[PDB]
Image (cartoon, coloured by chain):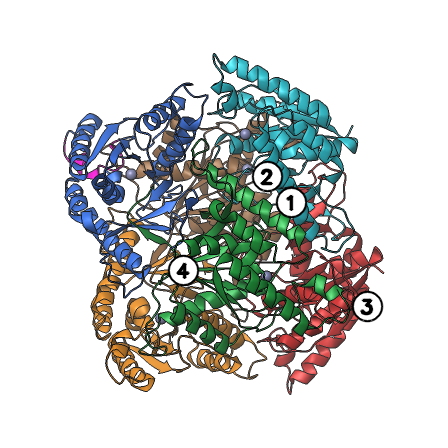
Chain colours: A orange, B brown, C blue, D green, E red, F cyan
Amino acid sequence: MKSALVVSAHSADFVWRAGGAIALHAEQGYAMHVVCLSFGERGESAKLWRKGEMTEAKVKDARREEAMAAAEILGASVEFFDIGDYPMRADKDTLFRLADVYRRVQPEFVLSHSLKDPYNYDHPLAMHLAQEARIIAQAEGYKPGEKIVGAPPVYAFEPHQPEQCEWRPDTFLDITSVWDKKYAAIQCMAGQEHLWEYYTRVALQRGVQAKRNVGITSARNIVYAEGLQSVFPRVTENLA
Amino acid sequence: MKSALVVSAHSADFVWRAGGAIALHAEQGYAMHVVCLSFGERGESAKLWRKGEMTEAKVKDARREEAMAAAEILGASVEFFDIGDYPMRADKDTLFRLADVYRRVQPEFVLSHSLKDPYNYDHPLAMHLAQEARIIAQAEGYKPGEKIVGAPPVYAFEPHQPEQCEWRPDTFLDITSVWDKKYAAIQCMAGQEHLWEYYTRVALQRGVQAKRNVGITSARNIVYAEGLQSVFPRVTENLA
Amino acid sequence: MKSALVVSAHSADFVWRAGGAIALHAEQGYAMHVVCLSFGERGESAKLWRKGEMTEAKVKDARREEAMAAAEILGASVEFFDIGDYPMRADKDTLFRLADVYRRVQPEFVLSHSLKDPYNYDHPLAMHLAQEARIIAQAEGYKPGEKIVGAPPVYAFEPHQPEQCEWRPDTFLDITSVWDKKYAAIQCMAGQEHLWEYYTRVALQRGVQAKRNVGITSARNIVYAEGLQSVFPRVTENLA
Amino acid sequence: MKSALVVSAHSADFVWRAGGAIALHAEQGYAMHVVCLSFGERGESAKLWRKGEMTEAKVKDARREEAMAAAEILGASVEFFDIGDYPMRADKDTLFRLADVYRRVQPEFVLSHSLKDPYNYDHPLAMHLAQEARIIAQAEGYKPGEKIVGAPPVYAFEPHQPEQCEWRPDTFLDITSVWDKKYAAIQCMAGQEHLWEYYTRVALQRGVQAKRNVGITSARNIVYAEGLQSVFPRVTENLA
Amino acid sequence: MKSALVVSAHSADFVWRAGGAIALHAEQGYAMHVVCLSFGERGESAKLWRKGEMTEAKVKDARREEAMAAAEILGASVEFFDIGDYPMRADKDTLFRLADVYRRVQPEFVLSHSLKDPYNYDHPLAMHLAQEARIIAQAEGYKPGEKIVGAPPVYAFEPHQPEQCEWRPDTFLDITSVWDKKYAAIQCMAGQEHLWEYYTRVALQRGVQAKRNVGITSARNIVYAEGLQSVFPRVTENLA
Amino acid sequence: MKSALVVSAHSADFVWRAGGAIALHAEQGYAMHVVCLSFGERGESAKLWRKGEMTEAKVKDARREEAMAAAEILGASVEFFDIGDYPMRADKDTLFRLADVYRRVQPEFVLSHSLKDPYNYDHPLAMHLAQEARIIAQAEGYKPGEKIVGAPPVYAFEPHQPEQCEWRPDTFLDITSVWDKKYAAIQCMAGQEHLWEYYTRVALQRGVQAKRNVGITSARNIVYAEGLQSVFPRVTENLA
Ligand SMILES: [Zn+2]
Ligand SMILES: [Zn+2]
Ligand SMILES: [Zn+2]
Ligand SMILES: [Zn+2]
Ligand SMILES: [Zn+2]
Ligand SMILES: [Zn+2]
């Protein structure tokens, strides 16, 4: 089956930043798989920590259930490496774990975080894991005999503060046809209504910009979009 | 009819740098049109100037005939603004001339030079003309009532010294199926065999790199490629 | 009196991009002055051109009245160089005209466009005029005997597509206290409701980002902000 | 009390690069705290190693006494993590140590090294520690119940070879009023007279440049300055 | 004796990327030394892994023999750290191992990989090791009493995809006089004829570009060149 | 004879920024030629404008005499295009004038201003003239029959605020042996003692940095240096 991979540093990230891309490609017949490296239990769970008698285990449970609910709505499978956030740290074993996901999923493309992020050190680490694991999975000397990975395009989805991250979308994905799914997944992020609104505005802004880049008087109905920054040059037979 | 536009600073440039793209899209049913802003009569015609009793008029004639022969082979139409090279200079009238080409051709995409070039000031000027004329042609206040231009992608094709020009190909066009046409067009560039060889090596190098970026063990037969740098973000519904 | 200057390529630009900054500093006792180099009569007036029997003179009249109405609401004075858009072109005389505005206004700071803009060549030209005129006005050899200009900070306000323009806000101006004025000025931009909504979303997005950069749990009520990119290093006695 | 933090890779760095900023803010009522991650015992102590029978313990003692003397003169407190230089290496525990300093000091701003430095790998590591520890200290899941850190601005002070480090000062701090203190602290750096002279020239050069950026004919008496590069966008209500 | 150092991530890299530089300086009386950090046994040995009953030990043996044969042809000595590729990882001990090579060889210059490489994470690690070990070897506190290293220039030799690596050659080394040696060394890379051809084309392309940068009508016979990117500013008494 | 060229936007610039390079190469047997495009009569002559009854003609006379005196001391010839400063503007004729200087001088290298300068628009214009005129002079179609120019290296000498200009010295010229000449030339810049001191400090700072880049314990006596940024890749047979 056609497949693709999302590598999310914290469990909520794939929902804010990749929900549209996931739902859209699922409807195109893709087996979308999400790896959440951590749950954002320490640094992306303020509401929970403000309740009494909170624990990391309790936070992880709440985050896990939200992610599974969102994944179901979007049409993706999801797994949890649970390696911890703030700080997130990985070793060779994390890397090989992720390379094995690549070997199993054989994704056509990969979505992860920007390589710079002055607001969150965990985010670029996730993308570095995603990229290096991809290359390990290409090596005929890694678990010899296994089917190797090819060269799936890798993209950074939109960070919270794109210019501060030196991130530029060179690719707009029109997610207008699946906005309802992305927003329903967004609503699984309990207690984070301000972010619901923020990422709604993001999709609308990128929607207008995407429309501008196909011609402002075009009849195409581009209302919601996700911006992506490509890691690799694309290969094509047509320049339109 | 489907159409596209190449803006060449000097008459030979579209052959070295865009021959593949022209021949490839022509076979896809595109009316490919080339504008040569000048003939490279002063700065790209050393062999001719080394003959006796040479004149700019004589050089232009030789360059014009070569370009027309190459265009015929590639399957493009070509016109000559004849505004002079070394130095190439343009005014509002040049700009409007080019905007009118846009309005007539209604291209789906545009190819021109890199925006930096420490070896040739004429080259970025050509691309600035191409880009600004494109925007003029978008304006409903420019020749009101005429059909406006949309937002065709613009690409810089490969300069002679790409790294010195700070140029990076983010797009590889597989021109393997039309290499014979590009090379036959190249052979119209009389007396420039060293450049024939140089741009053959360029296509082979980009071919290997393009192949690497689809997976080195892929069965795709990518032997010759042209590298392009995109000016604008592309809009799509699929990330593969 | 304390004063400051906005240099707008087209008459509507200072409203979308600087309305907050204008209204905010006016309330601080600044004589805010706006120069509109053109009216955007050819490239920023599509609605008007779609009416019958439209002329540039008629478009300019409509644009002029809108700008004057917006300026009144924001608390700024405004003048119109009327040098034409799409393409906007300037000569030494335009430059000296603007240098004379500097000499008269003696602004404490200047707002204008980003220095790159792949969607609009007029915009960077406006900022280059603003910057060079500022330097001319510094010269004791320019109209000797006149009081020279000092070194007012210069900022680029937010372009429509900030990342494509390689623009990063290094400064957020909290305009929460004057949002009603900016929005009322925005409503003077007749027939452009989609842009009303776009720049409302911009202010809300920058508002959230500005809040993030003072501490997400801070009691400061930062709801609407404008992002600016500084041209020059600032000089201070305190780093908080 | 108002407070601020300096993170110095080696014990002498805060004296050369931040002495002015420390003395200046101390006089403004700031409790200035300095963390020296190491003493520069192996790579910034050549004079000592040229004496006979030298040891790292002896070097550290000499460096510690100098730093304490300088801190006293500048009006700062100082602590020593003693994690070793050339190479400096940190782990999660170093990170948490520093996050605890943040939680205790609650600094209004942070000064540390440039993020690139081809002459000293320890320097960017110090700044990465400073930045990541700051973010850990923001997390309500890190030592839950403790008062979290907000968003204090972070600045890179001037490296020895600023252009090679790709460092640009976007902020000049006028330290004219405390130059005598900075220079007295500098003189605690025993045997390093060439560096005394170098960083005197640095302050004078930045002084002239800062003066240029407030207007060369301004009456402001800016003689000595420190240049800083900001990590985050600042938030303000005034653009002068 | 005059000496210089090449730090190669995988055993084959110094042959493709530095063979010319090695052979050329050897003929100038340099003791050229190569450190191969790994053999590229897992990620640069596909042909071998496609044979039956292959092992990492067997791959390393084959790679070692090739490297020794190439080194002999080029006129260099070579040693093998054998720390493993895909992923290559280093610790303080690797670093000190390399610093000791510096102390022993006292190289006049160093060649290693580009600092970015989206196709191979091992490559920048090698260059970071090379650079940091160089600085450790400068420290009078590292193995006190030993002769320290000065400031040998460091260069990144050409990566497979230079623009994707953001690599620009600021230095061309004319290797025309030793091309036969480089190519004979290249032929030791058994079964990799496509790469023989690729790096032949690279040398020819850089040859043409180097010739262009000394004057296209110069009598200098520059046919084969290697491109290098310098890490540090060079110091000279002549600007020709 | 060996020769080289300096293109100075204003008459004083070659003294502050290139005096060392001029004196040093003159002693190596170079015929050093300086073109001053203007006298800096309007924007670099404040002291004169503060006297009574000043005129541009009077300022130009004073500037001309200073430049001629400095040139004599440094060992260069100098000519004055007198095209005006603040604003400096050039046309095709200026360009051809400069190309003719190239054809006559046949320089081995060229020194001019940085390509960015937010403090002075005239400076980059001078460098653009220098670069484009160089290329015109290469063209066998420009004044056919004349001896063409080859590919002399072009360098930007140090601007007043290097980091704000995004300028990095990749080349340090040791001018220790001619500092007395540069300083004597500097003293011809009547009434500008603050700049005498500034550019003395610049040379001392670059001197220390150049020394650092040959090894801090080297016996080389590098006290005064000029920093240069190269436009083109250099071609060499040795990497030390
Ligand atoms: Zn996250
Ligand atoms: Zn050309
Ligand atoms: Zn506009
Ligand atoms: Zn240090
Ligand atoms: Zn390798
Ligand atoms: Zn000047």
Residue that badge 2 annotates: F158
Tell me if residue F21 comes above or below residue D13 in the rendering. Answer: above
**Cα distance, mark 3 to mark 2?**
46 Å
> Which is in the foreground here, disc 4 or disc 2?
2
Q: Are marks 2 and 1 on the same chain?
A: yes
Q: In which image quadrant can residue A168 be found? A: bottom left
Q: Is residue E40 above or below residue E200?
A: below
Quadrant into which the C terminus of chain D falls: top left
Mark 1, other Cα within 10 Å: few <14 / some 14–19 / many ≥20:
many
The majority secondary structure of the magenta stretch comes to loop
Asked if labels 1 and 3 share a chain, the reply is no
The residue wearing badge 3 is E72
- State which image quarter holds ligand 2: top right
Dot 1 amino acid type: Arg
Q: Is label 2 in contact with label 1 (beta carbons under 8 Å)?
A: yes
Q: Residue at x 21, y 47 (%)?
A: C195
B41 lies left or right of A151: right
Which numbered mark, 1 or 4, is in the foreground of this view?
A: 1
Point out the image quarter for the N terminus of chain D. Answer: bottom left
Task: Work out whether residue F144 can be spotted.
Answer: no
In the rendered structure, find residue A229 and report the number of the disc placed on it: 4
Q: Position of residue A240 (x, y in %)?
A: 38, 52
Q: Nearer the viewer, residue C160 or C28?
A: C28
Q: In the rendering, which numbered label is found on residue F206?
A: 1
Chain of the residue under label 4: A
Residue C168 locus on image (x, y percent): 38, 51
Q: Amino acid at mark 2?
A: Glu
Q: Residues within 10 Å of mark 4 (few under 14, many from 20)?
A: many
Q: Is residue C44 magenta?
A: yes
Q: Chain of mark 2?
A: F
Q: Nearer the viewer, residue E6 or B74?
A: E6
Q: Nearer the viewer, mark 2 or mark 1?
A: 1
